[PDB]
Amino acid sequence: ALVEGKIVQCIGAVIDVEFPRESMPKIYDALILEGSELTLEVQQQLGDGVVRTICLGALRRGVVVKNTGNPISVPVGKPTLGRIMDVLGRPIDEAGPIESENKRSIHQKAPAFDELSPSTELLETGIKVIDLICPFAKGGKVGLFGGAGVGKTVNMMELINNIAKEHGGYSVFAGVNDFYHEMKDSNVLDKVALVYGQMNEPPGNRLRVALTGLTMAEHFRDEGLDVLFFVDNIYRFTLAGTEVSALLGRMPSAVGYQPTLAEEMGKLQERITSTKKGSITSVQAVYVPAHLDATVVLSRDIASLGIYPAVDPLDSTSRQIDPNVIGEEHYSITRRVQQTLQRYKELRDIIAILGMDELSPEDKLSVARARKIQRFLSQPFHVAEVFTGSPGKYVPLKETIRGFKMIVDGECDHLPEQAFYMVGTIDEAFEKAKKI
Ligand code: NA
Image 1 (cartoon, rainbow, N blue to C red):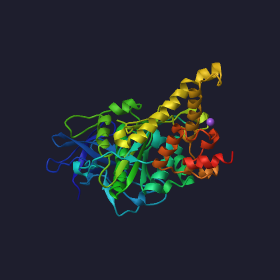
Image 2 (image 1 turned 90 degrees about the vertical axis):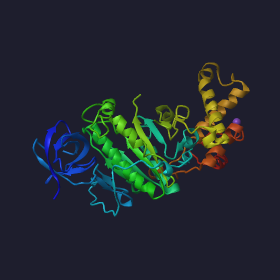
Image 3 (image 1 turned 60 degrees about the vertical axis):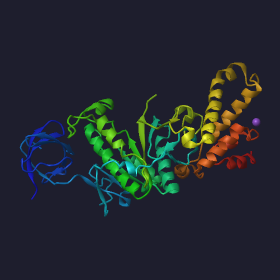
Image 4 (image 1 turned 30 degrees about the horizontal axis):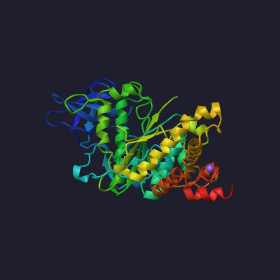
């Protein structure tokens, strides 16, 4: 037997349901219906025996439902890798069941204070421009800003690739055949678990999509791993609003009022952190038409110039650019690199108006060095090997720093600029120069 209840009012997916005074559901209990795929989840004690719930999926006044007495639990771990699941952890890729010995509740306490990693550490991506200009912290929150055509997906895929290859980590994607086949075709699919919501659904369901993704990321973290959690257009293509209307959209709660979706998401952020065991670092894709720690800004203009990845090395940002976190040398090189690029930008019209021979000795050096910097920021990607034929490169942070230091210190002033294009370490630039 399961304790039973009758629906009182439906006003959207919010479904107030009445239960015996003798047996009230607790917050987060999942209620089910004989013969329906739908699940209702308890949010609130309204009082006098009623609970407010949200319906997950697609119920008239007076219909009877059962309390399971348990929250929603989803399969976690390695059997989720390479699979596409829905918000309740059911397979939607038609590849059959997900057989795991481990399941986890989608609602979890944040880690206790003594489980938190005391100090800030970089998550090394192996991607020169990110590690130099907008370095990620383990447990940090990254924004990836870009329109279409600018490699947004390629960059996500390479990050998935590199964290698995070099650090033994995994990724989880929470979003809403296309992306899927890209990852099979680039062989990163087996390194990432996917959870999809749906277009046209209410904004509060998006919270649950993110909660399911996060709970999966947390299992991998508990295996002692560094994990990437990708969230793609999670406030977009909803029923009730736009993006910003979805954010201030209220929902039912046990907290003493109805908090915003923007407010329930902030609580989810508490679980994105670095612990003594491992870390979860989030990457939120933000769609641009022409509490973050780092912003990766993709630009059509950099891509026009033939530079991939098309990261704007002056408009991208990171709070980790701080000598106390990255050391004096890394901080200094990042800064000198940006000053040289900025100086070149400033000289752009004078080079046009009054010619390159009109520049002073020092300004000629700045231009030459800026151009070589722009080229050394380009990088062949492992996930383009399928398309292009050339091997991708993973560049350790020590080498990124050494390479760029050599350029600003003037120890590469004798190499031609073409030699710095589409290589890895600076030693590859020297080798490439010998053939040019
Ligand atoms: Na030169």
